[PDB]
Image 1 (cartoon, each protein chain N blue to C red):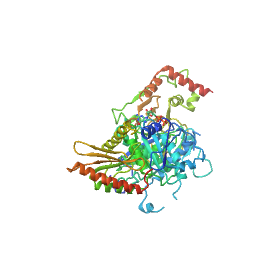
Image 2 (image 1 turned 120 degrees about the vertical axis):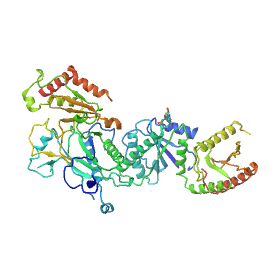
Image 3 (image 1 turned 180 degrees about the horizontal axis):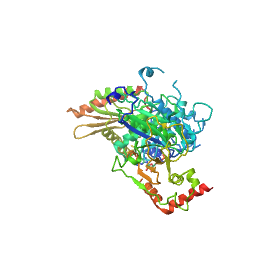
Image 4 (image 1 turned 60 degrees about the vertical axis):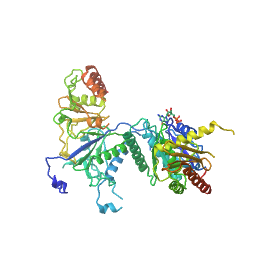
Length: 280
Length: 322
Ligand SMILES: Nc1nc2c(ncn2[C@@H]2O[C@H](COP(=O)(O)OP(=O)(O)O)[C@@H](O)[C@H]2O)c(=O)[nH]1
């Protein structure tokens, strides 16, 4: 599942790649950037294998600059992308939206959606669904957008959801995330809504873990961080680059008993995750 | 009101009251980059696509809603020069699909403004679209409604504007009433009368009886052309000099226009050419509110400065001689 990043020059593709993937199917592979300038597309210039090898195409639109020509170029790209392979999920990121109001952001997304739909109606493409995400480097939005894009390319999503829901229901876990060690792109969660504050807490917990471990090296990552109110944050490395970070509440119970039952349950969950080849 | 709101609007009597009305003008402005799919025939396809989208949005009954090729769109016919020259041209003893004793310059149909079932009511406006078009004459689309939601019509206008802007053109909105009546309706509106510096009917440097027999307002029309305006009243009687086979009547009513009206190609200002050579100048407040004051003041300066108006009139005389 290799995703292809496409956009106009100076839209921010390299900056997104540097921020996310630098700080197979599921691991954060070396993605392919593609600088696409306005021109006439050559008909079938040995690009069929390239677009057949892309699991999901991602388009980047700069909200600061004018973007009607960008939408026209995007529709031109989709016009052969959907023709070559009818199974590609198509993603559009409205990047550089840090300095915009909420009403302006919603109106801009609605205008972009309407323009893309009208252009696809003019080009005669039907049965295509293009997703849109308001992304920016300076906040959590790009991480969540890549999380949704990656989640669309894991066929075992509902089974991981059931496994995490069962783990949470039997360990008094407030919220459990299945992060990856790089790029902080959470792969699976429960049916509970992904709170932004809790996501940032877990991501900066990942950062603290990795930095502290890297400070003392050259002699399986496990972490218990307990707060004042008894709420604990737990880290256990899963298979390959995956790791599990769970916010667990004590609910007025013994700290060590809760830690022991959580450790046993999470070890059981990792043993179950060993059977399914969700890693890498 | 209750009679026409119940479906009894076929009384065919000229009512003294009017419903909500909106008049939209298509103006050729600029070709977008790429979209090659000539800059003078892509706008023809743009108007054809706009008319096709309008006629495709026809309100239909449930029996025709459940069923599944519709008739082709009516043709828009193009010409050069004043409209009366084209009217005195159909005499040709050939064909019958050419502007065919009152002449309906437009045709009307009921539309289905909310197709998605967004509104709980039934939405139905009425569109009037012309049957003629020139690159030098602006295009008219009219929306008449009585009880529709004034947001679904706004996004319908937005869809039309986007469909235009994929091609060239630029859809603008202008007040339905004349420019000369805005002090008699809206006293706060900006409205300036212009007595231009050089009178071409009596100046020794610019005077000819043959020219005034040919084109009386030739200097004024060239002044409006060189300052970036398009004729709004294409069916008036102040510019052309020919006859007619009885009066021409639009699909919405008789044209009650005192003077010829002009729209700036940007869509921001409206001018009006009087009989005595004076002009009326005002801004389009609907375009400004929906979406810029130095252009109208610069035009006022050019119409009030002797040197610049002299230069434009000299260019007009030079083009007339050569
Ligand atoms: N404020 C802001 N600027 C951004 C963002 N993303 C990219 N940029 C700007 O984009 C520039 C980098 O663009 P770059 O990645 O080199 O474009 P590319 O090479 O075509 O992919 C930087 O100078 C940033 O200022 C963002 O989310 N917020």
